[PDB]
Image (cartoon, rainbow, N blue to C red):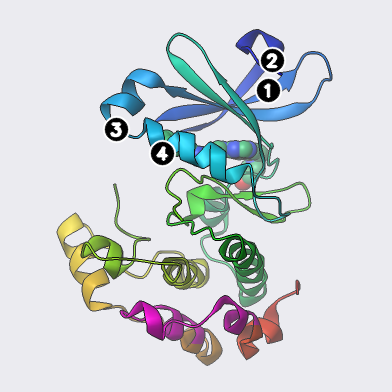
């Protein structure tokens, strides 16, 4: 298993990333269909993030969960690093938001449950994501949600970052609960709650936790979102309490 690019047939582009492209691919020997993410050494090195990727690969390979995207392996050549990923045939939740605009409560609750289960397992293995956002949420063949990208895990737009990360503070696993809250809002409304036209204004609004709801967001959803988007990490609920929220249980199709 000392992989090389010549072991795969490369197919169509699945996405364009900051640091690299993702392509569909097929391993020649087995015909195993997978995704291949190609990052550039020169660009990671120059941005000082090459280590972060040593860490991701190290971390994501101790994780095994149906709502976390698998990293099967990795290799590299003169100038590029390749991640061999599980292929998620239904694409990103980002693209799904574009197509649909916003999701009903049942899709939203179902997705939060999947996320919360995934993050609970991560927290139990002492892992914090730090980078939950719809681009990094992939959909398996049955439409099951899959967390992608552990490039920023430990232990650009600001839209999904909590106050303690933008205000330059110590953070912990409650980072991921803020993220749930941002996503729960975005799913129901179709834009994240602190969205603005400038970095400076978005920063301001995250820092103050300044957001409002459209009249159509139901009271149960407002309750859950408000509990998650607390400025103080320690006032945010545990993952187990998110899963027990009556709005989540009333509306989720998964357990
Ligand atoms: O970059 C990372 N780390 C890192 C980077 C730099 C420095 C340090 C760390 N990590 C990282 C970041 C992101 C990823 C996810 C990459 N994208 C994908 N990965 C695996 N499978 C995938 O499948 C897709 C995909 C699959 C299908 C698809 O379209 C299918 C057909 N569509 C379905 C949707 C409908 O609206 C229209 C028709 C579109 C995309 C994307 C994808 C993986 C790893």
Question: What residue is disc 2 on?
Answer: 8
Residue 240 belongs to magenta span? yes
Q: Are marks 4 and 2 in contact (CB under 8 Å)?
A: no
User: Looking at the image, is 91 positioned above or below residue 241?
Assistant: above
Residue 25 is marked as 1
Q: Which one is in front in this view, the residue at disc 1 or the one at disc 4?
A: 4
CA–CA distance in space, label 4 to label 2: 26 Å
Q: Position of residue 246 (x, y in %)?
A: 64, 90
Disc 3 versus disc 1: nearer the observer: 3
Q: Give how far apart the Cα atoms at labels 4 and 3 are.
A: 8 Å
Q: CA distance from mark 1 to mark 4?
A: 25 Å
Which region shows up in magenta?
A: 224-243
Q: Which residue is mark 3?
A: 48
Q: Which mark is residue 52?
A: 4
For marks 3 and 1, give the CA distance.
28 Å
* 10 Å crowding of disc 1: few (<14), some (14-19), many (20+): many
> Which sits earlier in the primary sequence, circle 4 or circle 2?
2
For label 2, count other residues whose C-alpha is less than 10 Å away and answer few (under 14), some (14-19) or many (20+): some
């Amino acid at each position: 298993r000392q992989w090389a690019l010549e072991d795969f047939e490369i197919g169509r582009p699945l996405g364009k990333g900051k640091f690299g492209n993702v392509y569909l691919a097929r391993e020649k020997q087995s015909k195993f269909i997978l995704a291949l993410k190609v990052l550039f050494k020169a660009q990671l090195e120059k941005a000082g993030v090459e280590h972060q990727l040593r860490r991701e690969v190290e971390i994501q390979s101790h994780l095994r969960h149906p709502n976390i995207l698998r990293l099967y392996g990795y290799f590299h050549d003169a100038t590029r690093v390749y991640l061999i990923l599980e292929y998620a045939p239904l694409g990103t939740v980002y693209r799904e938001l574009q197509k649909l605009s916003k999701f009903d409560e049942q899709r939203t609750a179902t997705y939060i449950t999947e996320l919360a289960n995934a993050l609970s397992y991560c927290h139990s293995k002492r892992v914090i994501h730090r980078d939950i956002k719809p681009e990094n949420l992939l959909l398996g063949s049955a439409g099951e949600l899959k967390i992608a990208d552990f490039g920023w895990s430990v232990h650009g737009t600001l839209d999904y970052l909590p106050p303690e990360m933008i205000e330059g503070r110590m953070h912990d696993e409650k980072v991921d609960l803020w993220s749930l809250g941002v996503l729960c809002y975005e799913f129901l409304v179709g834009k994240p709650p602190f969205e603005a036209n400038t970095y400076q204004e978005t920063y301001k609004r995250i820092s103050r936790v300044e957001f409002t709801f459209p009249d159509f967001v139901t009271e149960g959803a407002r309750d859950l979102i408000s509990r998650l988007l607390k400025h103080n990490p320690s006032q945010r609920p545990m993952l187990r309490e998110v899963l027990e929220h009556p709005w989540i249980t009333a509306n989720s199709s998964k357990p």
